[PDB]
Amino acid sequence: AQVVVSSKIDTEGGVLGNIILAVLNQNKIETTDRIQLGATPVVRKAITAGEIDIYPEYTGNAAFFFSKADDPLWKDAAKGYEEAKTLDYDANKIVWLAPSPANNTWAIALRKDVADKNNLKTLSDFGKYVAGGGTVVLAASSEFVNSAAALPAFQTTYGFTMKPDQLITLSGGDTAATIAAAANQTNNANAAMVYGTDGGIAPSGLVVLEDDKHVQPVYQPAPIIREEVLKKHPNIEELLKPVFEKLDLATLQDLNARVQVGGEQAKTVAMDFLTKNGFA
């Protein structure tokens, strides 16, 4: 009876899915590889229909599965995890395992040189810097600039206001174009809209600022597993715990970069991560 391991179609889906598969095979659990099956909807239907067994899900996406998109509890990491875990077990008998501390949510990343020079690590620091007349040009989508949940919420909470001459506004939502603007300083860009663990952040020499007042919902990746399968292989829980523990924001960025910038296979990158940290 094979454990069917899967993931979402994106890079991180590939990386995390292979870490799970590698760890399972490494500890004598026979597996079926259905990694990168499709977007979140297809993968959810799959596990709830019993077609897959385990895959990496993000805490905050449970906001959308259980019709709680507008709830401010998802902006807290601990409460988001506890809620995702409780709901899925009660509703679906899906067990959420120990999460990664990485937060793959909408964020602002700065060029390292500007961050170092001005001691900017958090959005509180960034807001003070912008408010006080600091030099910034943010590359962002029109949706990020304008939708109430994004930059307007950052602006309100951290106490700054972006002038039109501090903004490069792009039509699309792909963070590839925004990361490259900041990386290459197009029209003096020095800051970029990103998702926390985008691979392009590592090689571009950017740093993600901490969302220290919790304005965006938290999307921490965790392995989630069908209960009947976990009952058969109960050691899966403890074996994935230390592994996901070690998957911080920068580590995740680098692994994703190895795949989406270096063109390495997700399988190889997963195994290299595991051997490097003594898990295989």
Image: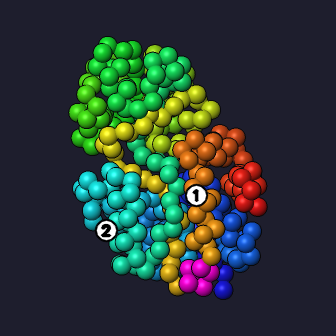
Q: Distance between the residues labelled 2 and 1?
A: 25 Å
Q: What residue type is labelled 1?
A: Phe
Q: Is residue 232 magenta?
A: yes
Split into 4 quadrants, where in the image is the C terminus?
bottom right
Q: What element carries label 1?
A: helix
Q: Residue at (40%, 61%) from the top-left corner?
A: 81
Compared with 89, 218 (above or below) is above
Q: Residue at (26%, 53%) from the top-left corner?
A: 72
Q: Residue at (31%, 68%) from the top-left corner?
A: 66
Q: Which amino acid does label 2 sit on?
A: Phe
Q: Is residue 195 magenta?
A: no
Front-lying residue, 247 or 150:
247
Viewer-side label of 2, 1: 1
Residue matched to label 1: 244
Left/right placement of residue 213 relative to residue 224 reads: left
Q: Residue at (58%, 58%) from the top-left corner?
A: 244
Q: Earlier in the sequence, mark 2 or mark 1?
A: 2
Q: What element carries label 2?
A: loop
Q: In which quarter of the image is residue 232?
A: bottom right
Q: Position of residue 169 (x, y in %)?
A: 36, 28
Compared with 113, 32 (above or below) is below
Colouring scheme, one of rainbow, by chain, secondary structure, one colour? rainbow
Q: Give the range drawn in magenta.
A: 229-234
Type of secondary structure dominating the magenta stretch: helix
Q: Where is residue 163 in the image (x, y as percent from the top left)?
A: 28, 20
Q: Position of residue 270 (x, y in %)?
A: 69, 55
Q: In which quarter of the image is residue 31?
A: bottom right
Split into 4 quadrants, where in the image is the N terminus?
bottom right
Residue matched to label 2: 66
Kindly tell me whether residue 9 is visible in this rendering.
Answer: no
Kindly tell me whether residue 26 is visible in this rendering.
Answer: yes
